Image (cartoon, rainbow over all chains, first blue to last red; front, side, top):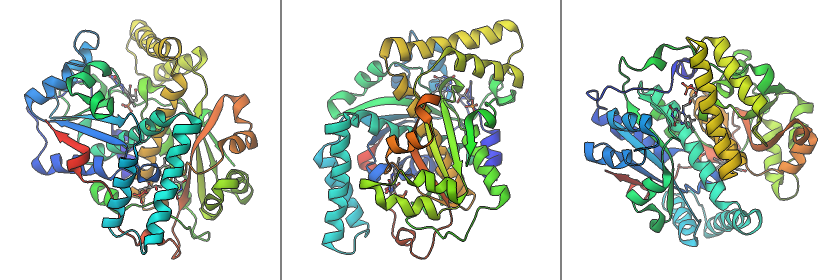
Length: 216
Length: 216
Ligand SMILES: Cc1cc2nc3c(=O)[nH]c(=O)nc-3n(C[C@H](O)[C@H](O)[C@H](O)COP(=O)(O)O)c2cc1C
Ligand SMILES: Cc1cc2nc3c(=O)[nH]c(=O)nc-3n(C[C@H](O)[C@H](O)[C@H](O)COP(=O)(O)O)c2cc1C
């Protein structure tokens, strides 16, 4: 069941480059990225899915030099996903989101729609104006998406590793992200592990629930 | 089929208070919280799982003021999880983590263990001493945990809603979290939706991939 998946999945240390996602799989990973939940359905994200050798090479520039171990993971894997967050939440994005909810039939009336818009605007304005944490707020949503994604791709029977070990300034510049209003946070190579993946056979380690968990 | 799960899950707006998790389910949700990944296996989190009437009422003090719409969700669900992040990363936590990985048998040699420790410390130091973003870094891991959790609980056939709409100051004070070194980020009621959950029958809405996703 899904608990088997949770207990069996791992962070892949090495990928077999000859194993490629099926066409179906390549679509499903995109479906996972798209359908993650987010606060206010704000969806404050951009994904780059590199499946060509040259696409993956562009992402792997971000690891060259200081993050050399990350480099190979990015090149060997079939598909490599860069999760990016918005750097600012603009009125244009807020309107885009509510108008899509409208188009998808989520509002019975014009009043329902305007209430939804107003509530989202209030939440966004609070983060920006008062808490001064809108960048962080949006990045948190991208991380939630990542969590969703790692379980999803494990459940598809795929291997993956989340990577913070890359240079976001280099990745941002490689893809012109800053001027488009995004920044790269996590890279996730997806594929099938090789026999050089020593982590595939190691026991999983987590702290005991008596440390991390209180029942009331 | 995890894709079906992702496409069919939703944020529950109303719970049937008579429908409780099975005993086995109550254990599975705890397994999902525990076995999420995190950067460096840093596991910078504390969970409160409220399953009693008194426990849920304590959590629902946080649904005051602007957040009164969260109150019923927190009270009527079977189980309510509070995701908390550490407020600071300490060397004691770092040691706790590596010693657990050692106990679980992740390290062939003393050198392997010390290399793992030193790598974790470098990453942690970069956050807390250079970037000064360790609070955000750890919160991002908690949000990853949340995303894993929402898909997992949906795959168990359970309903849930992630809530940022609560007063963290009140929830923190109610549970003495600040002095214990934690703060509350997301509340997730888990259970079964009622026929009043209007969101169960509404269409799901996301932005189109031609906005959110580039293939390279
Ligand atoms: C946000 C994030 C960043 C990570 N960055 C790296 C990375 O840069 N390199 C790496 O080898 N593993 C990385 N990991 C993998 C973790 O070490 C791993 O998730 C953790 O040790 C738990 O093991 P598991 O993923 O096999 O359950 C990262 C994990 C997460 C969640
Ligand atoms: C971090 C987070 C916080 C949220 N906070 C709330 C909340 O306080 N109240 C609420 O009714 N829904 C809340 N939501 C639900 C979102 O509106 C929902 O995820 C989004 O509209 C997408 O719809 P879906 O979850 O049904 O796919 C939250 C979602 C997330 C991811």
